[PDB]
Image (cartoon, rainbow, N blue to C red; front, side):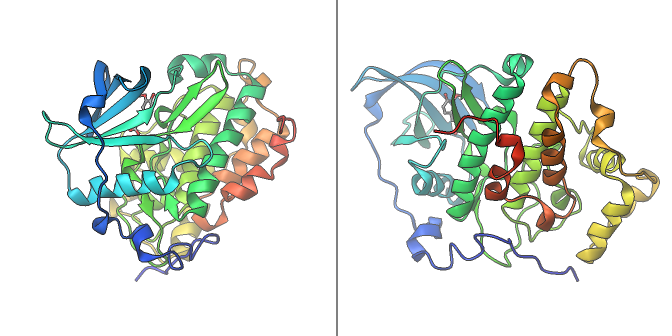
Amino acid sequence: GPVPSRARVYTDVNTHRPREYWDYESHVVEWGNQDDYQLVRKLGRGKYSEVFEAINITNNEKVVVKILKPVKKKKIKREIKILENLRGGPNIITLADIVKDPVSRTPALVFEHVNNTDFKQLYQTLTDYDIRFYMYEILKALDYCHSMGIMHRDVKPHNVMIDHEHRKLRLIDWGLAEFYHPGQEYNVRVASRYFKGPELLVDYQMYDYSLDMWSLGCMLASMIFRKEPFFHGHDNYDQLVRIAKVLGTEDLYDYIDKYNIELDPRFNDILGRHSRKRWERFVHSENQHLVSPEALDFLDKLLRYDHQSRLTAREAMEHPYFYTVVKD
Ligand SMILES: COc1cc(/C=C/C(=O)O)ccc1O
C-alpha cells in the first residue's frame, strides 16, 4: 500500500479547533434578505454555478452574486463554512451575504465586487515588479487559509481577481476548498488540468496544502516565461508527461517510489525517458525582462514532484525574489 504523508506545517490546526469550525455538514446557514440584491448582468457560468454582477439596493453598491447549481448540500455547506471561516483574512474574497434564490431554489452567495482586469490581457502587461507584487499578495492569502486549516485546491489565474488600478487582489471560488485533516484521503479530481499537482496526476490521495504551491508555481512559470498555460497537456495523462519532460523522469520515479505509488500502466507507452531541464532554456528575448536568478530559484523551489519538498507559503514569502517588493 501507499506510504502515508503529513503536511509539514499547520498539521493539527483543525484537530485543536472546536468541532463547529470544520464540521461543515452541521453548519446552520444564516439567510439574508434576497430582495436586497438586484441582478444586473451575467458574468459567467461554470459547472457548479452562475455568477452575476448585481446591486445591493440597501447601499447602492456593486456586488457579485454566485447562484449555486444543484449539488450536494454537503458541498454547498462546505464552501459557505470555509468562506465564513476565512472572512476578513488577507486577500480572501469577502462573503457579504447568503440568500435563497427563488428561481434556482438554491443558495446565492453575495461577494464584494472586484473591478478586475481579465487574466488574458493583464498578463500581457504585468511588469517584473508587478509579478513579484501580486505573487506576494497571493501568498498572503494562501498562508492565511493554510494557517486556518484549509487548502484551496483550485488555484489558477481565473480565481485570482486583480483590480490593477488599486493594486488589489482577491482569491476567489472556494467551491473546491477543503479542510486539512492529518491522514485523510482526498479526491484527486480537483484543480484545472494545467495546475494539477503531480500528486493528483499519480492518484496519491493523502495530499495537503502543498498542492496549492504547485498550482502557484504553474502560474508563476506562465507569467515570467510568457507562456499561458506553462504545462499544456491534452489530458491528465499527457499533463504528467509534459511535466516530466521538464522535471525529468528519474525524479518522477523517485517520487512515486518514496510513497510506494505505481504509475498507471498506460504511461508505459507515452512517458519515455527525460532528463531534468535547467530553467534557463525557457528564457528568450521576449521574456528575459521578467526573469532573474531569484525568479528561477523561487520557481524551482515551488515546482517539485514531492509535495513535501515544496516551499510552504510562509517560506515562500521569505524568498529573495520578494526583496525588491515594497512592504509597508
Ligand atoms: C467574477 O467576478 C467576481 C467573482 C467573485 C467570486 C467568485 C466565486 O467565489 O466563485 C467575486 C467577485 C467578483 O468580482
